Image (cartoon, coloured by chain):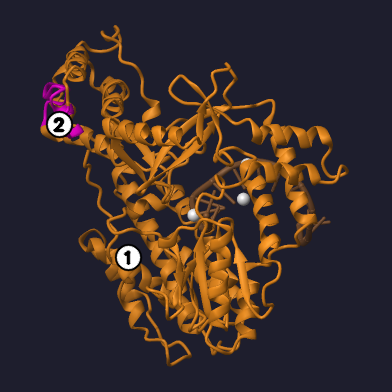
Amino acid sequence: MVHYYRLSLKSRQKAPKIVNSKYNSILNIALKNFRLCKKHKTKKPVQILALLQEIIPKSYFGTTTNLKRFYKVVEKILTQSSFECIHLSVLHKCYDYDAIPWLQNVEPNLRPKLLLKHNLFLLDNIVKPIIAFYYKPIKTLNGHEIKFIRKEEYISFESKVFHKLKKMKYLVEVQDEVKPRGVLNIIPKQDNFRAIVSIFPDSARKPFFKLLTSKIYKVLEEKYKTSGSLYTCWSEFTQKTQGQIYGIKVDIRDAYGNVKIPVLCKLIQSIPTHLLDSEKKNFIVDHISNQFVAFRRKIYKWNHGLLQGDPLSGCLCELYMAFMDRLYFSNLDKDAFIHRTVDDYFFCSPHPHKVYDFELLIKGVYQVNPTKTRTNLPTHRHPQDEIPYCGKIFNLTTRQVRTLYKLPPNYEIRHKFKLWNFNNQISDDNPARFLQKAMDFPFICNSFTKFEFNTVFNDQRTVFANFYDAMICVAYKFDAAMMALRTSFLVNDFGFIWLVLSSTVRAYASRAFKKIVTYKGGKYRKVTFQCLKSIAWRAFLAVLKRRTEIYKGLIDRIKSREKLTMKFHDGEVDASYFCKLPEKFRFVKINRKASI
DNA sequence: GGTCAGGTCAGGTCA
Ligand SMILES: [Mg+2]
Ligand SMILES: [Mg+2]
Ligand SMILES: [Mg+2]
């Protein structure tokens, strides 16, 4: 019933010094070297693969091919995605049992389970602990990517910023024995850091916190009418404005930290008693007024703004910023466009000076991140026509909007897709359910909306390029899923690949059609259902080509058998873009190699 | 049977 092994470190166990009667004594040799390895200073850089080869005797696998099979799991662990799993069957299936010396005495039909439990034993008591001993996993928050850093380096970085947080009196030792609400975590974010609190589980009170969060959001509904859909605001303003659009995006820095609690507390108290009674009012007030945080076996008062990671901080910060909005942006030219997400403001106007004035307005009220500022003002140092905002790329000159893709160079795209679900597991004999759950539409649903498929302000050329780019992503997910089928399902029958493959292509083109015609626009000429199918299949073509020999059968099959049109009813579309791979996805890395 | 509204779950988006 349980077919999965989680790759994550927290699964690890603490090794006994001696193995029990149900395990073969060879394990104790391994454990010995483990202990001795821990006593190594290991000041210089270390490769975990290497140390394991000097911890687990080759005599345990016997043959190099057996050893390589096991280390291929170790490699997956060292390069793991959050939530990633393998099939427990991987740990015993396809091994050369003749070459394993300590298994010759036992009858053949009992060897796989034995090998499984011994390989499980090494993974839980030696492999994961050794990775944990020298490294800390931090989640980059780009997809499910996990970066490992040396414990010596993270602790120094965590100590440096801890002192900074003490000298600036953001963190102040309380020394009153007050109960901490959670543990402070310092996480690395580029050159900076993020101080957040991980809240101790509060089973009997988070129902209460959902109630207070709900009531705050009710307050934000009643006062301050809705901001507009971002799509409707960009639609109307583009229709309104016939001249060259001018715009700016500014990034407010540390919005949670720059909230003035005294001002926030007065907003809380001013809520009408029918909305929020005085007891609840006062509970929120001493909640944000007494933030207590546990660092290294010491309790501190967080004294700078709102605590990130706390459940109330989001709605409470939104309430503060909503109040700041009218204090300073209630009166702006109504022929202008403005939108705010949480700490990001996007403002556009046909007049440059009003965009210029907006930058000064915002800078006078808030501390911003100047490197994160993007603007088409001609005078500015580094002007651009493309403004990234809220997951989209807005071209102020063309008015076209494209999806924004966060794929740094050398990012491993398999981190974008969570293909394993521990709560609902798929057996190693059932590969098809795995692949089709992978191709559930919901995962790309956010790039199949009116914003990318409208023709109101969007050209057919960019609506196509949007659909292609999304499909490129679905291909990359298909690809990652295939490697999962190869490396842990160990499938040999790839015949079942086609049905859902093209079965997904159909529905995706179909899913696009209904959106596109639901949001017909003035630039809409004519788009053929079949053209979307030709685009989807050409998207897969461009991706599947990265590992041609593995898929050369597949590429040839649909390359010939299936039909590529690109005769869409528009002449502007280069159609050249569809044949190749967009530069964004040329530079992403689909192979797995350990580096720690 | 065919809807609805509500509920769960899921992999995704925004800061
Ligand atoms: Mg929640
Ligand atoms: Mg920011
Ligand atoms: Mg929010």
In the rendered image, residue A207 lying in the magenta stretch gets the answer: no
Gap between marks 2 and 1 measured at Cα: 36 Å
In the rendered image, residue A48 lying in the magenta stretch gets the answer: yes
Give the residue drawn at x 13%, y 22%. Answer: A57
x and y, in percent, of residue A492 in the image? 29, 48
Chain ID of residue with mark 2: A
| Stretch of the chain drawn in magenta | A43-63
Give the residue drawn at x 58%, y 17%. Answer: A176
Q: Is residue A177 left or right of residue A385?
A: right
Label 2 or label 1, whichever lies nearer to me, is: 2
Drawing shade for chain B: brown
For the residue marked with disc 1, what is the amino acid? Answer: Phe
Do discs 2 and 1 belong to a common subunit? yes
x and y, in percent, of residue A226 in the image? 72, 62
Q: Which chain identifier belongs to the orange chain?
A: A
Chain ID of residue with mark 1: A
Mark 1 packing: few (<14 Cα in 10 Å), some, or many (20+)? many
The kind of secondary structure element at disc 2 is loop
